[PDB]
Amino acid sequence: MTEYKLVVVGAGGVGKSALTIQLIQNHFVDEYDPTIEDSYRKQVVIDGETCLLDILDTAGRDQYMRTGEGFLCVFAINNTKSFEDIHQYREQIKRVKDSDDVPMVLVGNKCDLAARTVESRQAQDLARSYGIPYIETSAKTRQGVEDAFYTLVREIRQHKLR
Ligand SMILES: Nc1nc2c(ncn2[C@@H]2O[C@H](COP(=O)(O)OP(=O)(O)O)[C@@H](O)[C@H]2O)c(=O)[nH]1
Image (cartoon, rainbow, N blue to C red):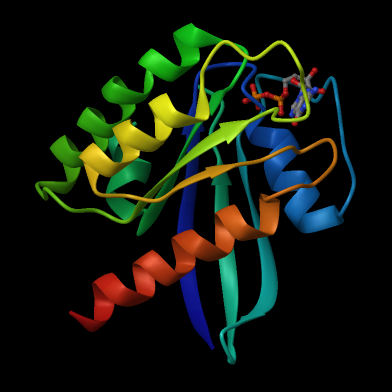
């Protein structure tokens, strides 16, 4: 079985744990200890291929960035600061990876909220500038969660095939 090492990064509070748990347990967890950092695994079928996702839920290290094959760069659509922090996360990943093109997906979480401060178009354009996909999600309603992680796996698959 093919294993995919995924790393979820982003400012505190954007919903990294909630996203990971929703994927794994299919339910919305709030108030999850913000200081806990661990990896979660799930065997799934993506595009006819059975694989094992190994997801590191970061809490805030080039060590794990080095081992990671793909990265979910998450920000919250109602927190502009988390969006601008994306640049820094991507720079760190590229730095330790010594590569210009590392599998990455820009995730705009909390799309269920009405008070949006980051427009989808802004993120879309930034992602396009980075050459990566942009996917809006909601760990609360689960909208786009599977899309986010599965898209990253496909990015990794394509990266490996090159
Ligand atoms: N409305 C809404 N709140 C969310 C969503 N995802 C996470 N949260 C809330 O945001 C807070 C932080 O989430 P958490 O997963 O702990 O953030 P992290 O620090 O990135 O791991 C919690 O209070 C969650 O309940 C979401 O999609 N929608």
